[PDB]
Length: 116
Length: 115
Length: 115
Length: 116
Ligand SMILES: OB(O)c1ccc(/C=C/c2cc(O)cc(O)c2)cc1
Ligand SMILES: OB(O)c1ccc(/C=C/c2cc(O)cc(O)c2)cc1
Image (cartoon, rainbow over all chains, first blue to last red; front, top):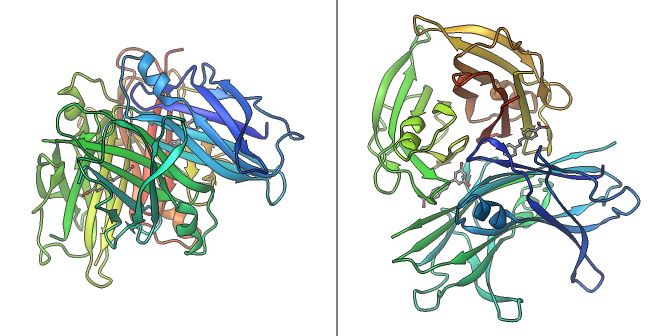
């Protein structure tokens, strides 16, 4: 798994389950092209977004749909979503974990980048 | 001052000074149009971005140029920038502070919304 | 004001008001002796804890009563309190702001140390 | 594993490896008694601190030695350590993950609490 997303809920102390995630990749014309999407599992994890072959060098945006997550719990949150934008694989293939910790008016995000 | 942005450095324990910040408002065609911008002060703060009259309900994006900040310090960072996207809502008098706490591979952001 | 404490609420997007805060200084016997305390203001801030003369180098603990804050809101929290333990060091004129951003099962804290 | 600790490094974008962790439990006389200790692995995880039988109801403190971690990397950090204090198992047995994300002048901590 070259790219994994993990989402946690800071209000409930739980994984954030069924969170929609959309990944885009910047194209040659500077537009964002759809690249992959999915939703988090019962463990707050989203695996299988892409493959080693498909995950080439580029600028990627990981959009986490936090607003829909909170609304389903009856909370009206501040943000529309949480976006994570980064250059990937420009020094060769790496494994990326994008983690986010969510609250209704705040979020934290970090990356764990490893060389296989 | 209906909108203020505050940026802090989690590595050095200081305000993040001279950081470029751009604010955009979502247009009817779903495109991001420039709304306001500036550079954070010595206290890591950016004031005077807009006025009560101009800051109507809508979807706004605050883009913080974190990459340039870390590069200026010789530190290789993860993110191209930090983006904060939110809806402004009229529900009594509201002032919005968007705060961001920066590290090379991580950031936190919160909103402090007061009367 | 060599030491200020600022507490924010990540659930409601507001200052955390009327939060009890206790500051301790580590004694020679390795026990925590009370140093200063108060309750955060309407802006989530606690000023006037100490003076330049009293705030000497040493190890300090700031304890924030997060549990009472969440209980007052009907929310069951994880932590008994939030504790921030640090050394004050003389290295030119320093002012310390200890900030904390609170959620029911999580908190972030940072130090803003300036001249 | 009723109690696990996970530590991440926000400067390097990596697990925080070889971080010392000490767990204490409040005794009847209100003193902190040593309960368990260990250090994080190459994945930033610390498993096997305790057992279901030993991890009874109580108030626990998890002390993460962040200062020693940073000093070994040549950084002089702000905090002495990061402390996490919580009541455990007072509504019956739960599984606890205590996570922390570290920077030299800041840290974030969250808990993931699950019912097996
Ligand atoms: O079970 B796991 O593999 C696991 C469990 C918890 C985390 C938490 C990460 C995290 C991210 C943040 O942005 C802030 C924070 O305090 C913690 C990661 C992996
Ligand atoms: O105008 B002020 O006096 C002010 C306003 C907001 C902050 C926010 C701090 C903060 C701390 C964290 O640990 C995490 C985070 O996202 C933000 C600080 C000072």
